[PDB]
Length: 314
Length: 313
Image (tube, rainbow over all chains, first blue to last red):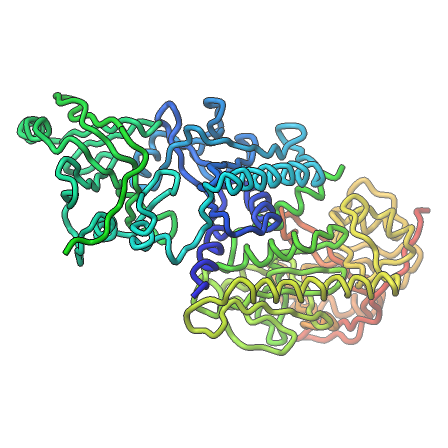
């Protein structure tokens, strides 16, 4: 059933448009490239250095490449969206902090290290657009950048081609032997990520689970935003996670609890699927416990970008 | 400059999608075609034989070619459409008459001579969509059909390349010597079409104007739908226009005016631009007065698909 791929691709270009020129440019890039061994995502939410949530119009996870259409603040379907200058590698289009806290549950990644190519559609801003030839040129050079990046990856043999069918299947990651941040790993449920490390579980309703083959490490399925029970945060670089609770008493009894162990946590963050609005779990890294305290609560630093996997235990 | 072309194309593929698969197929068709000498329109409103309003996803006016994606009735972002079977050359997707009455002022054309290509995105519905290779195949055969159509037109030299700059300029049609139905002629204002036939005008507020070089003909700018003052209709073929008024009395007093007045009318219908929602005037042809009576009112049949144009006096 290759149809699933079709579905995915379709819906990606079937999103309601944020920008006026977005549809044309994105569609032309995708179609002219016509290489579907490369995974792509449209309207990818990212976190800026200032903690504000922004978005990029086209995103290749394997190549870590973003593409953004540059229009003025004029011609924008979403009020309020924001057009502002940000750190050099970060997108111009951001969300107001008012709607940024409503979108917490969304799948939001870190742009650190990623490159952003921009397409400037206005010859004279505001108003009059540039000619089609120029735009097509920009699109062409961008495509060649993408292709040459892909080649740079395949020659280094670090390039793993995209398959929808096997990517949500734990067995393939067990076969790989490791789960990496570069592999951009998101699994459909807790039982799956549990089964990566040797569990046989049918279903898992709990937030955490102990690593079968390592007692020092704990598989964690946290909400990295604030909710009813907890206040959790993650730095824009993804290096540091802070954990607190709404009740200070519970944090107080969780203080010693944190202090003794397990000191390591493999983190799979609960995020909404960009399509079909369902909960998924993304691997954020392997973290180690740094500090115990009031206010900010527990502090976890990311000691590893990869964790080894295991065959089921019996 | 070319910026107008750019803007047009952008907005054409930037329409809010009616269908879930529309964006992908249409955009891929346009880009893979990559011939921008070919004018195209997305979500073109058309009139069926039964007077219901339908629409096609991609339309090339020069080639008279429509392209429609078949997803069936299940996935529709618009619950304001209806899926039913119609004549072989007519689209599967129609609008309920409730909102069809909201779409009157929109630009709606005649499909009678046009051909429609369909893209089936479901191998067998219900359920699972078809694989990408099949879809790409359909899109390709459609594209090469387009190319070969364009070639049949350029060899017959009936092909006028698309130019945004000159298409709304009366001077080009005056130079042409004729305004034709096949040329798909639409002008931005009444003063322009007036100036096509020899008038010199800063602006024109009137509903109609007498043809300068023929006392026989009247340039008319009717709303071909029903409004406050008048009740007007046009057959799906575009052959017959009926003119009545909400007041039966005014129709009765318009009887003598019609029978005595000029028997020929060059008709430019007032329609909203598919983009930017502004009033535009599309050339409907040359009509001749057939009969006037109470009830049904005046009846005009179309005697010509092209009309001669003239230099100013």
